[PDB]
Image (tube, rainbow, N blue to C red):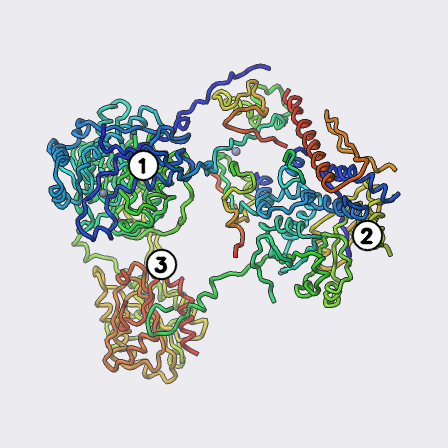
């Protein structure tokens, strides 16, 4: 009976409101002028058709209550209409100069052919007679949506808006933009609300560089400018040094600019997930913005012919969710790019559903294992930003030139490994160190199975010194040496062959220290190969079915032994685990049918990210492209196919 | 080897059963002591009691629309019959039994096409290879019963051997569905699939059949049969008459009379194990898990009575006059309507006790 | 939770097959772990 | 204001008919399991009157959690009773 | 009792019409239900 708590209204602020929407049929008349028949077979870089295609896709899912796709005010229950009005010249002059406003003013009163020269002249832009009012509406719509969000009229806004604004520079336009839409709205809100809107965090995922938006706030600390794109400086538009990742601000805006450059195209979901997991969230929480502005561009979607990427619309919702978690709930979305209307339609659909409140779905591929170039690219970005921000120091061992004379005093470590190696080999497998007299080499250069002069099948396994995995400490800089292992790679084969009663021969060739490519190793390899073949192999009475095994380099020795001798009668298979190295072309001198026997009896495994395939000759001899990287990975992977090819080649 | 599992009905099965006793008890009394005829009356009475015993949502004179069959939870199906719960129980008993290596096959024999549609509607998402041996299957799956160019001018193509170690095999226990109608019209449909045990969902399969004796003789052991045994029913008198040691119409009348006289069965048996019993059936042994009830001993039962609810006040007219199929359906219809009004409005006021 | 989880996995073999159990309870989830320590369809995590 | 001014005085045709929204989350409410009868399990105080320091695993816990919810309008049950007419955001589930 | 009765009378029902989606009650929550089937 006792009324303990009288009933009260629920006390929440996010989602009793609706999602802001800005849409006009008045921004579809800024169009190009017909020049040549080639325009009929090109993707039409910035076309007015982008608006109504997406707007059609919306009403098909019941989120918008409009059965005939026309501008109304009763937008349903999940979204709220935000009216647009032509922005006065003052808001535009907040970023731009006075001559660019008069440029667009004069543009309004041009004839046809002068507009044609204007389209032809611009840095990838096009003008039109209806390009003044249709350029004033974007900036105004952006300011209205951002006011609606900041003053809490809507929980969040989304604005389908054209022409773009992320390439327009304060001086003049260039890059299919007329007025810089992001910068105008950001400066007008920081001027209109410098008590609530005090720190803004702008993010760019459009695949070009937001050069104008960069310059607008390159000396601003209230505006954290973040841009991700492909750089490819020589060719890829804009091709400016402002797109390079070292543009980290200047003056008071130092550390408050960030360019993220993709070394190559073709990225997917895992890259974006990995990156957004690592970098944007610490500097975002440390920067603590009062508003996060989003400069959306769907010119890199799956099904786009200009971006050539494979990003799915689920990752878009994930990143939308992350940015919604970043800020206090205030969020604004302006659209900049896009070329393939169906990809931009499905992506905008996913983003709008997440903006109404739906959770992001699970990604179609959680396992792609991102390309190596982007990794060290982000490492260099982390170096700069660790120098600038604190959330990257002490956690990545950054904390914000060895010698050249102590090189005479160095620890050898080839012979130590090979000696330890020799030790644990002889103590379990009783390998015979075979002596190469009249050649100055380490005693443990080669080790063979005992009674080698009677075994028919002799497997000759050549390889360099082994690989080392070491643990680097993360607390401070350098690597921990006592916590390292030797990655013995050629061990599975030695055991395998001893399980099948074969002549097994170990061959180590050390590495030329402080040397890019082990050329002297290749020379010494040809010497050991030729010498061993002449002085020892031809004097063993019982011998048949020789198979070679090459790891990484040293295959020049085998190539030289094949080209400069005739030894294919007793050997029946060559196999090299190239990995990543350059190709050893066979130079046949005895005869040419040896080269075809070579190409035929061969299996070579080279990496996915190798120099090729981005088609080899038969002088390389039936190479194959792996799916994984690393010598250890591909050897443990294809250890069975290799023994299969060997056993299939023999009886 | 034949075996029997004593099964009873549920609440609403007894409600609709008493609805049937109201609509037919005067007429069946007249039978013992072109609208329709007393032959058709007694046959419809018999068949409808058997149908109410097998998921009473089949009592409608309409096929299930075949999209709703696979658009429903398993509970809503087994809420109808008590037989379905015991059935699904033994299903989960055998698929979650301890399994050396056995890919054991069973055949389930339904009575008509409606029941078998419900059967494929129940075990579709389960861990079996289910094959309906009669036409118009409900989502027929294709489970089949048991019995590198990278270069040019060269030719190795070891992809074949490579592919042998990548692609996998299914292991679901086989389960076959059909009706005894087709098993009488045709034969040897079970002779091919050598099964270890037969669960006859209908308890009147008349076991010594040519298609079944060919399998019995083919087998080295004795093939165990399971007849789902209703405690008292228009089949259970004849089953009583069999397990020990025209004319079809009189047998139907006599067993329906034994059921109506025996619908007030005070004793029921329980404590049926399932994993032990399915093991008993698997190794083909007669273990005592089956219960030896075998019968119940025989005016006073022509009066129907529904379940008396709190503040309910529902009664039946008992239709003491002629009957025609249209009048039958409208009578049964509005009787189920007032039964539903009674169950809804009855329940809709009991909240406030618990509230206070 | 052991009773509950075993009911979900045994009684729903058509829509749910892998679950994750989290224990941010600062005492370690002793009894819960042993019931699914040999079990692979369930990934148990305990913060403690 | 503008002269772009797309004028079309005609009854235009329905293109997308109204459809009920295809969302799987929140036309529903949130499940809630509260039962007063899990508050039996109490210690039998045997040493002395330890009533300053009773058992930490306590029946009293459930009530305070349930209480704080109705202080924010989430539960419109005034006496803090687990009854049906809780509210609109959540939905009580019976406990057997 | 009430839900068993109501569920029975609600669907494909008896021969007369005297009395006779969102939210997905008819086991149509699309999280690994149709794709759980074999579908050859
Ligand atoms: Zn651009
Ligand atoms: Zn604890």
**Tag nearer the camera, 2 or 1:** 2
Q: Are marks 2 and 1 on the same chain?
A: no
Task: Give the chain letter at badge 2.
Answer: B
The answer to whether marks 2 and 3 sit on the same chain is no
Residue B296 x/y as whole percent: 84, 45
Task: Output the chain of dot 1.
Answer: A
Q: Residue at x 72, y 24 (%)?
A: B311
In the displayed structure, B181 sits above or below A568; it is: above
Residue located beneath label 1 in the image: A282
Nearest to the observer: residue A465 or residue A218: A218
Judged by depth in the image, the label closer to the viewer, 2 or 3, is 2
Residue toward you, B133 or A395? B133
Q: Which residue lies furthest to the top in this view?
A: A2
Marks 3 and 1, Cα distance to the nearest angstrom? Answer: 32 Å
Chain ID at mark 3: A
Is disc 3 surrounded by few (<14), some (14 to 19) or many (20+) residues within 10 Å? some
Q: Quadrant of ligand 1?
A: top left
Q: Is mark 2 within 8 Å of ligand 2?
A: no
Q: Work out whether residue A447 can be spotted.
A: no
Residue A201, above or below A614:
above
Taking B106 as reference, is A152 left or right? Answer: left
* Mark 1 residue crowding within 10 angstroms, few (<14) / some (14–19) / many (20+): some
Residue at 81 percent across and 39 percent down: it is: B25
Q: Which residue reaches farthest bottom? A: A541
Query: Where is residue A569 drawn, in percent x and y?
Result: 34, 82
User: In the image, which disc is placed on residue B239?
Assistant: 2
Q: In this view, does C13 lie above or below B347?
A: below
| C-alpha gap between disc 2 and disc 1 | 78 Å
Specify the label residue A628 is tagged with. 3
Give the camera-side residue of A302 and A407.
A302
**SS of the residue under disc 3:** loop
CB-based contact (under 8 Å), mark 2 and mark 3:
no
């Amino acid at each position: 009976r006792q009324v303990i708590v009288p009933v009260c209204m629920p006390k929440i602020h996010y989602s009793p409101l609706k999602t802001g929407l800005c849409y006009d049929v008045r921004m579809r008349y800024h169009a190009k002028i017909f020049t040549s028949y080639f325009e009929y077979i090109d993707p039409h870089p910035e076309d007015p058709r982008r608006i109504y295609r997406i707007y059609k896709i919306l009403a098909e899912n019941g989120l918008i209550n409009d059965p005939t796709l026309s501008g109304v005010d009763d937008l349903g229950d999940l979204m709220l209409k935000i009216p647009v009005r032509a922005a006065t010249s003052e808001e535009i002059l907040e970023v731009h100069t006075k001559e660019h406003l008069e440029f667009i003013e004069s543009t309004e009163k041009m004839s046809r052919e002068e507009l044609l020269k204007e389209t032809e002249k611009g840095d990838s832009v096009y003008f039109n007679n209806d390009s003044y009012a249709s350029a004033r509406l974007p900036c105004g719509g952006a300011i209205e949506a951002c006011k609606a969000v900041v003053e809490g009229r809507v929980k969040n806004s989304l604005a389908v808006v054209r022409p773009p604004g992320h390439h327009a520079e304060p001086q003049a336009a260039g890059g299919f933009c007329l007025f810089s839409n992001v910068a105008v709205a950001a400066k007008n809100i920081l001027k209109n609300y410098p008590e609530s809107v005090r720190r803004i965090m702008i993010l760019d995922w459009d695949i070009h560089h937001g050069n104008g938006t960069q310059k607008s706030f390159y000396q601003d600390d209230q505006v954290l400018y973040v841009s991700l794109h492909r750089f490819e400086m020589g060719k890829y538009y804009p091709g400016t040094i402002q797109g390079q990742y070292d543009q980290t601000g200047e003056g008071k805006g130092e550390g408050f600019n960030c360019n993220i450059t993709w070394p190559v195209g073709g990225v997917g979901d895992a890259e974006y997930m990995w990156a957004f997991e690592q970098v944007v969230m610490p500097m975002g929480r440390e920067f603590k913005p009062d508003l996060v502005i989003i400069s959306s561009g769907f010119d890199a979607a799956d099904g786009d012919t200009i971006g050539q990427c494979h990003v799915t619309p689920s990752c878009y919702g994930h990143m939308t969710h992350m940015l919604k978690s970043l800020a206090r709930g205030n969020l604004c979305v302006v659209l900049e790019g896009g070329y393939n209307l169906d990809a931009i339609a499905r992506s905008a659909l996913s983003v709008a559903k997440v903006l109404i409140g739906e959770p992001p779905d699970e990604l179609p591929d959680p396992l792609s294992d991102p390309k190596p170039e982007v990794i060290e690219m982000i490492d260099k970005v982390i170096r700069l930003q660790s120098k600038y921000w604190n959330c990257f120091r002490r956690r990545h061992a950054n904390s914000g030139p060895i010698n050249d004379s102590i090189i005479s005093k160095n620890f050898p470590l080839q012979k130590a490994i090979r000696q330890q190696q020799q030790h644990y080999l002889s103590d379990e497998f009783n390998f015979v160190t075979l002596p190469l007299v009249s050649m100055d080499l380490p005693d443990n250069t080669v080790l063979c199975t005992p009674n080698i002069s009677e075994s028919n099948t002799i497997i000759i396994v050549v390889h360099d010194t082994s690989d080392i995995w070491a643990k680097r400490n993360v607390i401070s800089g350098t690597i921990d040496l006592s916590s390292s292992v030797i990655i013995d790679n050629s061990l599975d084969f030695i055991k395998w062959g001893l399980d099948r009663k074969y002549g097994i021969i170990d061959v180590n060739i050390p590495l030329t220290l402080f040397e890019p490519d082990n050329y002297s190793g290749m020379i010494t390899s040809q010497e050991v190969l030729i010498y061993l073949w002449d002085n020892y192999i031809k004097y063993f009475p019982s011998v048949a079915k020789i198979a070679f095994i090459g790891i990484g380099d040293s295959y020049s020795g085998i190539v030289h032994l094949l080209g400069h001798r005739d030894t294919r009668a007793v050997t029946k298979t060559v196999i090299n685990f190239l990995g990543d190295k350059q190709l050893k072309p066979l130079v046949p001198l005895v005869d040419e049918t040896l080269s075809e026997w070579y190409f035929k009896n061969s299996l070579i495994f080279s990496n996915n990210s190798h120099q090729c395939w981005k088609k080899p000759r038969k002088k390389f001899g039936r190479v194959l492209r792996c799916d994984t990287d690393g010598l250890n990975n591909i050897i443990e992977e294809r250890f069975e196919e290799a023994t299969d090819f060997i056993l299939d080649s023999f009886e | 080897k034949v075996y029997y599992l004593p099964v009873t009905l549920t609440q609403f099965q007894k409600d609709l059963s008493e609805i049937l006793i109201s609509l037919h008890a005067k007429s069946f009394k007249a039978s013992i002591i072109p609208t329709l005829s007393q032959r058709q009356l007694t046959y419809i009475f018999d068949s409808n009691i058997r149908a109410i015993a097998n998921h009473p949502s089949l009592l409608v004179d309409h096929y299930m629309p075949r999209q709703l069959l696979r658009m429903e939870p398993t509970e809503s199906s087994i809420a109808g019959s008590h037989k379905f719960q015991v059935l699904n129980q033994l299903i989960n008993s055998i698929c979650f039994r301890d399994r050396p290596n056995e890919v054991i096959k069973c055949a389930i024999i339904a009575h008509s096409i409606k029941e078998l549609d419900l059967l494929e509607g129940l075990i579709l998402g389960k861990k079996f290879r289910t094959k309906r041996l009669s036409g118009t299957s409900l989502y027929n799956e294709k489970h089949k019963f048991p019995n590198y160019t990278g270069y040019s001018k060269d030719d190795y193509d070891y992809s074949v051997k490579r592919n042998l170690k990548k692609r996998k095999i299914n292991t679901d226990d086989w389960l076959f569905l059909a009706t005894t109608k087709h098993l009488k019209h045709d034969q040897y449909l079970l002779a091919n699939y050598d099964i270890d045990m037969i669960i006859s969902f209908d308890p009147m399969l008349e076991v010594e059949l040519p298609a079944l004796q060919v399998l019995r003789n083919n087998a080295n052991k004795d093939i165990p049969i399971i007849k789902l045994l209703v405690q008292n029913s228009p089949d259970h008198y004849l089953l009583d008459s069999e397990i020990k040691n025209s004319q079809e119409y009189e047998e139907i009348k006599s067993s329906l009379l034994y059921f109506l006289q025996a619908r007030n069965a005070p004793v029921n048996n329980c404590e049926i194990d399932y994993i032990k019993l399915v093991k008993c059936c698997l190794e083909g042994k007669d273990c005592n898990n089956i219960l030896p009830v075998l019968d119940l001993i025989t005016s006073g039962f022509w009066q129907p009575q529904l379940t008396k609810l709190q503040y309910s006040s529902t009664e039946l007219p008992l239709w003491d006059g002629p009957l025609d199929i249209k009048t039958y359906q409208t009578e049964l219809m509005h009787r189920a309507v007032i039964r539903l009004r009674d169950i809804q409005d009855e329940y809709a006021k009991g909240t406030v006790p618990l509230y206070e | 939770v052991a009773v509950a989880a075993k009911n979900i996995l045994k009684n729903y073999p058509e829509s749910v097959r892998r679950i994750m159990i989290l224990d941010w309870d600062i005492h370690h989830g002793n009894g819960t772990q042993k019931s699914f320590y040999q079990d692979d369809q369930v990934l148990y995590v305990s913060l403690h | 204001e503008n002269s772009l001014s797309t004028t079309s005085k005609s009854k235009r045709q329905v293109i997308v008919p109204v459809c009920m929204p295809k969302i799987h989350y929140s036309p529903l409410k949130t499940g809630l399991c509260y039962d007063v009868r899990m508050r039996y399990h109490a210690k039998i105080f045997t040493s002395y009157f330890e009533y300053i320091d009773p058992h930490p695993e306590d029946p009293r816990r459930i009530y305070r959690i349930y209480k704080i919810l109705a202080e924010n309008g989430l539960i419109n049950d005034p006496t803090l009773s687990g009854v049906d007419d809780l509210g609109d955001l959540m939905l009580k589930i019976p406990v057997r | 009792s009430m839900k068993s009765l109501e569920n029975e009378v609600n669907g494909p029902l008896t021969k007369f019409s005297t009395e006779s989606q969102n939210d997905f009650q008819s086991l149509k929550a699309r999280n690994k239900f149709l794709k759980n089937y074999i579908t050859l």
